[PDB]
Length: 488
Ligand SMILES: Cc1cc2nc3c(=O)[nH]c(=O)nc-3n(C[C@H](O)[C@H](O)[C@H](O)COP(=O)(O)OP(=O)(O)OC[C@H]3O[C@@H](n4cnc5c(N)ncnc54)[C@H](O)[C@@H]3O)c2cc1C
Ligand SMILES: [Cl-]
Image 1 (cartoon, rainbow, N blue to C red):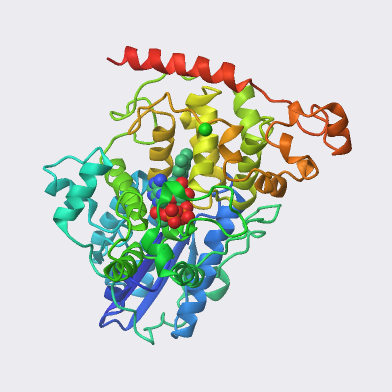
Image 2 (image 1 turned 90 degrees about the vertical axis):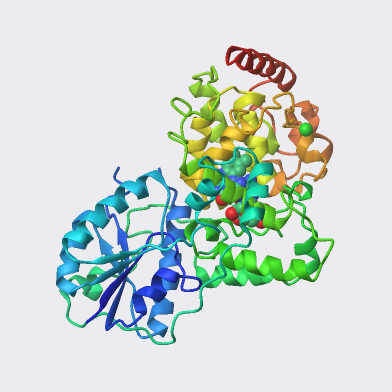
């Protein structure tokens, strides 16, 4: 008889899940599995992101229970767990969604070898990306496009991505009873307290497929907003109602299918002939993700500077004091510090808020390596995504993809154009809540009488600025110019 495992890693959803559909086909028993390394922390990861994963697993558990089944959260390393459960459960087929990250390729090769030793068929459909990204490279002559313009031309020659797969059946084949490795007490979803976090998550975005689909429907309630979306024109200071979809955490974990999102976009576009086009359109945003997955997966050492063939070698400074001030939201520039507080509190900030703080750290003011900023984002972002974090940090530091290092955002002026009253600053830096708007982006310029009346004395309640932007940005531009000459 057929006994199958559907192994979740990403792809934390029932919709558009061809791996799950294959596992269920003609099966007597299906074992839905997630493998949790219970020593992960004792090795880097904020409770915000880890709890988002746990909420996503709890949602899957509820969905499987509604269909007569159960999610099994196995503790250990895949290479140690799977040989045991292959034999225990009489497994004949293992299904999982393909993953192109570096660690995944090593892990999955090991599991494939073990499956073959046990006589287990392995099925690995592509559904985390819009397309088979190896197919895109092949149809481009064997190399990934290195500009968005050429990437968009390639996908348009290839055509539409595959349609989302059908929903799974209303009843699933359950795990077999009295299998020791499937014991309830050994296979439940843990809480954040149980995995060892001491402080609670503070983010406002809840994990899981159910929430992902609800947020998708909310975005599409206004088709004119979807059709006319232009990413560069959206407001980074909007926090009560964010100005973009905030689907990124859901896409990162696969709670939302990218193919479903794309299909829904095309439905709207067919009815709105003046809809925006790539790169600025909402379809364009999914193509930025696809572009960076395609380049990233075919480039060695993509997450590093040294040994990375697409990355310019730049003389970044090893300045721990500047990195600490940035990481701890005590730069003395309220726009920067508010965004860095949103990072640690919510784990998500608007794209142009990410631009502001990444420019400041690297080529704009402090001249610290983008790899250090990437590490801080990797800890705190609930949408942390290996290829997308690396690629956008290389863009913002003018190390790859982007080369216009004379464009430097002002940490004072940039936010003021959207939010002159500083509502965003006041929300995330309440020490400044009573500062008059005239000084809230530049509090060190307020007279002492004003600082005292506001209960915010610079140097006592809120730090002085760690640099003078005019001085620092001129120095950084000169160094970038010199670095660009050296790589001639
Ligand atoms: C320094 C830096 C680091 C970043 N790190 C990450 C990261 O770890 N994870 C991440 O998902 N995005 C990252 N981004 C890209 C981008 O800022 C986010 O995808 C975006 O803020 C998510 O908001 P949203 O879902 O509302 O996006 P929308 O504008 O609604 O876009 C829809 C989807 O398109 C994709 N997308 C949008 N913008 C980009 C982009 N510039 N690059 C790649 N894909 C994009 C995402 O999957 C996103 O959910 C980073 C950008 C910068 C400047
Ligand atoms: Cl600016």
